[PDB]
Image (cartoon, rainbow, N blue to C red; front, side, top):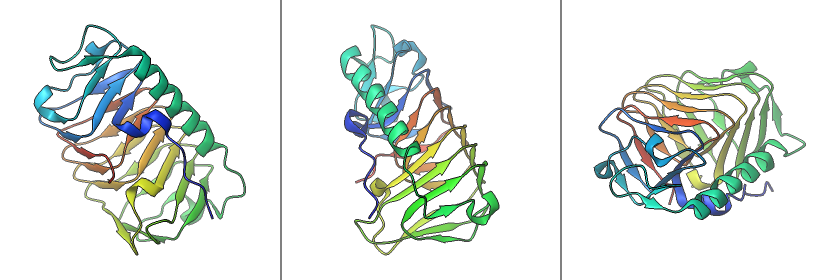
Amino acid sequence: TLDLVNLGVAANFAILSKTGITDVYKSAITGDVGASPITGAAILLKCDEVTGTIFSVDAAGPACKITDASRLTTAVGDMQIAYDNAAGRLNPDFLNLGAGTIGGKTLTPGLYKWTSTLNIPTDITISGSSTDVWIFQVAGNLNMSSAVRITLAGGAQAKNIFWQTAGAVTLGSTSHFEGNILSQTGINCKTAASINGRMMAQTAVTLQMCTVTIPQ
């Protein structure tokens, strides 16, 4: 059975990036947000958008920000370890499933690999027990189209799902995502996209009136 990706301190964040967090007001974030090593000024969230703590490396950032460089250093470090752990898993259960387009699929537990961009143009289901683990390894971009919903079935939980992407993630407007995103690059959410899962970007997270909730 497939081991969890250990996020270490990064587990405490709904959104963690390296070059900031942009926003089209109003978004709804539940969980802590942070960015390092970029200045807190690069977090463009207001205080009324975040239920949780906004962490900054410095004296800049939103009014409510807490300055904690040392915690953000560990979190981003942990996020990179998680990214490398997820990317490094061997012996996939699936390689190039749906030739890189997986709309309408029900995904069962295990390790999936794509040597391409992964596209999700229509609704999918992720189906398994409360303790089953999914790791999706994507060597290109990850695209989910407008209005596309990931459904969890069988007791599958968002905290047991990891999406590792070598390229940028693009969540289409009104889309509903489930799981942790470990992006080597950006995570770009469009108007009124929901994410039940963490957005861990080694560049930036961009929001457009999005809802982000840390998985429970």
